[PDB]
Image (tube, rainbow, N blue to C red):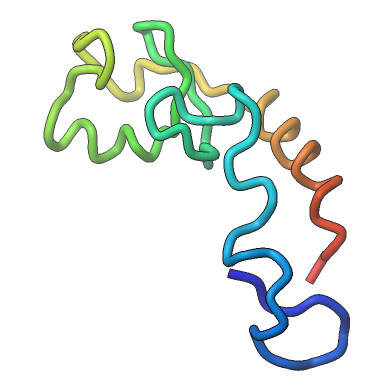
Length: 100
């Protein structure tokens, strides 16, 4: 949710930002092609789609085939995209102004 704002110790009351943080979705980029949710680890898959190496972890448990073009999906055979992370932390940072 959200600890607190200013050093002023208090409690999660005076609502001012729902229960999520601004950067909860982000443009049609940092968003998961499927989960549309902010990825925590953007990796490129052979099929040609970038998603969260996480949502992929389970994917291989109940379906080793891409969730999209139903294409055989094989972990380890993917390329990591770090040039993305930074970007995410950036554009989302300018909307944090709260380094707890």
